[PDB]
Amino acid sequence: PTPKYTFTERAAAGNLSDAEILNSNNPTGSELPDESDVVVGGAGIHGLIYALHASKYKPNNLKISVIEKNTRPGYKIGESTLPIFYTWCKLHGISAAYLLRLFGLKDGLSFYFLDRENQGQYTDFSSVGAPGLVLASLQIERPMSELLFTILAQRNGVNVYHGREVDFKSTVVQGGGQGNKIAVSRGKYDSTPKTIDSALFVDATGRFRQFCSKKAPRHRFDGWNCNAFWGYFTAPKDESKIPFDLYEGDHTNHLCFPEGWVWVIRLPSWEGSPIANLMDMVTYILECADAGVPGDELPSSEELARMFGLKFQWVTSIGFAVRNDVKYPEDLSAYGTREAEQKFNYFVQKYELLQQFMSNFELIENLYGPGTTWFIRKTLAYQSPVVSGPGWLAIGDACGFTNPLYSPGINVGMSTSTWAAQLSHPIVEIGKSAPADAAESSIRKLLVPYDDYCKSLVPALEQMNRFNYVCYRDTRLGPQVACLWQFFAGIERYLSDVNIETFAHYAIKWVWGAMVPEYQQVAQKCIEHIETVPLDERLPDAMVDELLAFSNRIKSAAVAADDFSLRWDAILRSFDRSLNFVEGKTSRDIYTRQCSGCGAWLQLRPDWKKCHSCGLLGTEPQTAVTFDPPLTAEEEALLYAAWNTAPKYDPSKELKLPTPTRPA
Ligand SMILES: Cc1cc2nc3c(=O)[nH]c(=O)nc-3n(C[C@H](O)[C@H](O)[C@H](O)COP(=O)(O)OP(=O)(O)OC[C@H]3O[C@@H](n4cnc5c(N)ncnc54)[C@H](O)[C@@H]3O)c2cc1C
Ligand SMILES: CC1(C)c2[nH]c3ccccc3c2C[C@@]23CN4CCC[C@]4(C[C@@H]12)C(=O)N3
Ligand SMILES: CC1(C)c2[nH]c3ccccc3c2C[C@@]23CN4CCC[C@]4(C[C@@H]12)C(=O)N3
Ligand SMILES: [Cl-]
Ligand SMILES: [Zn+2]
């Protein structure tokens, strides 16, 4: 496919604003429709996931308009995604060769637990991702992911309007047929507001809860909450002076300690690029995905930037997520002039390993515009008590949220998004096919499981977060209890069986394993003990012993019960095939390698001989994954065979669950 510069030239020809060039790609037009089946408030990642899944699940059934107040896809924190997300992307027709042009490769998760009372001592827990011929995970710049999903939605009969705001004072939401009158303005100042007559409103306004806040007060969990402060830094080509052994930039890295933890996410940034040019680049990529262009014949990220007149750089996202019962000195003016900056630099110097780590990185000023060198957000976790009602439902952050740790926000939160997408077809048809009272009663009944799932989901995620935090207070509990149980309970068993039809059902059964009983039992034992030790104290060694022995005793039984075959000793660097801790074990599979030219992390797979980021050829060797323990030629062939194409929808297969097998 020859590249076209349609939007770049349209924008220039008409001096189009950012919002106007984007909205000109809508099937129905750049202006709003008079009516629609579904109106989605907010085009963050979840609003777009919802609209894409709803149209893909049953094409040509619902008219869907997404209203987004930003003039173009705006900055968002929340950059790390997991295999279920990539699988969703692949099921929507975008595989790894194309996604990697836009996003950074993610090969698993890694944890380093810093001893507070013995500065310099640390332990680690490291896992891998998957071979390049299996799947990938992604580190995504959210203005790019939300552009990608805007264009893809527009190419699948979904209208998305940037630069338009839902007016929640004049909007009417009712439960009788198409009782909704959604008021859409360009802002408070707008004299000319429009109304979209519609059947169903979806509140996807994230943490702002713009609609469902009118139905219930925000709810907070007992005990401490968290704050976060973060910034953006260079990404070093040479990672070898990072002060942690065997550190790899293509993991989502977690630096953990009693007060909380630090995330480290390497990802490419497109900031500085005109929006019309990016529309042309994304559109070209989708046409190449449509055509099935092989990876080596697809232009590299940097080449795309040259072709479409874009800006491209490598950056590292680095942030603290700490408890809000931490004591700070009254005067922090020595560490900067903004609170976010102050508390960031103050926390770094409290840990020599953090200061040594941070000394590998250079701060970027105002990557996302003025005022964005530093970010702070306080009191992270919350839940919406009411997430549906006559004429409306909520998805994503608007339902609740906990913490960045293990990235439940996108990857678990998309269970609500995709389930709501699937449910939307009968909800709209019910209202079109029955009188008002019975329709409303049948819709209420249909949504009871969605309400119950949401109700119980956030508290389970909150207990998961506290479980990990309290264990982060000791360099044995962190890797050997918290991380071990999260990975055993939450690994995505039978993900290769998921398809568009089963995705929502599978996703709502995952919950990162936080519903698994033996998980919750160990989590409660640890929280009940550690929460009684004041934060500024070290856990007594006897408490660690007792919790470690308890965790391992529950573990051996739960592991035996699991009927899922898994080369555990190849996935977790510190553990054997039965998930026993092994003090000196370092053997593990190797799926990735760093480009000698640009520093970007690459997947090893024989049909990708060039860097997908800069286009430089590696030697014809390499590119061979290292399986340790080894795999035969046949065993490796059978592995990639299962992950090629997703199974067609079989209405009689039962769904196999991601969680471990129950005991007899
Ligand atoms: C510090 C931190 C780190 C995190 N890290 C991760 C991570 O690594 N991985 C992960 O998966 N998750 C992470 N999360 C969670 C993640 O950021 C969110 O779960 C995710 O962005 C939710 O997206 P959303 O679509 O629900 O809402 P958002 O992305 O917030 O989008 C809401 C949209 O609604 C729009 N809007 C609001 N009001 C109106 C109106 N009246 N009319 C029209 N539009 C409107 C806004 O413009 C906005 O675009 C993190 C969160 C925090 C705080
Ligand atoms: C299930 C999977 C997505 C996964 N989910 C994790 C969660 C936490 C830590 C590690 C993982 C992994 C690594 C896995 C294990 N599977 C072996 C056969 C195919 C696959 C898929 C992949 C693989 O190649 N690597
Ligand atoms: C298990 C089931 C009750 C179920 N539980 C859900 C939870 C959330 C979202 C959807 C579902 C469904 C729909 C299912 C999926 N199963 C496929 C084989 C038989 C069955 C039973 C039924 C079916 O026909 N429809
Ligand atoms: Cl993660
Ligand atoms: Zn390169």
Image (tube, grey):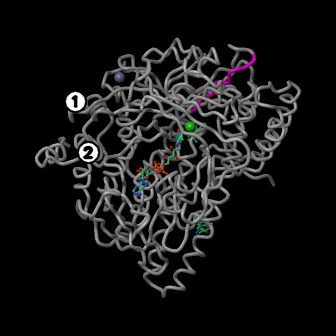
Question: Which residue is depicted at the point 55% across and 60% down?
Answer: 213
- Residue 374 x, y percent position in the rendering: 47, 30
Question: Which residue is depicted at the point 31% across and 51% down?
Answer: 151
**Disc 2 target residue:** 279
Mark 1 falls on what kind of element?
Answer: helix
Comes first in the chain, label 1 or label 2: 2
Q: Amino acid at mark 1?
A: Arg
Q: Amino acid at mark 2?
A: Met
Query: For this view, does 147 lie left or right of residue 422?
Result: left
- Residue 587 x, y percent position in the rendering: 63, 22
Query: Mainly helix, strand or loop, the magenta region?
Result: strand
Reply yes or no: does residue 115 show up in magenta.
Answer: yes
Rendered image quadrant of residue 349: top right
Question: Which residue is depicted at the point 85% across and 25% down?
Answer: 540
Note whether ligand 5 is within 8 Å of mark 1.
Answer: no
| Circle on res. 306 | 1
- Report if the CB atoms under discs 1 and 2 are less than 8 Å apart: no
Foreground pick, 341 / 127: 341
What quarter of the picture does the C terminus occupy?
Answer: bottom right
Magenta residues, as a range?
109-117
- Residue 584 x, y percent position in the rendering: 72, 18
Reply yes or no: does residue 112 show up in magenta.
Answer: yes
157 up-or-down from 162: above or below: below
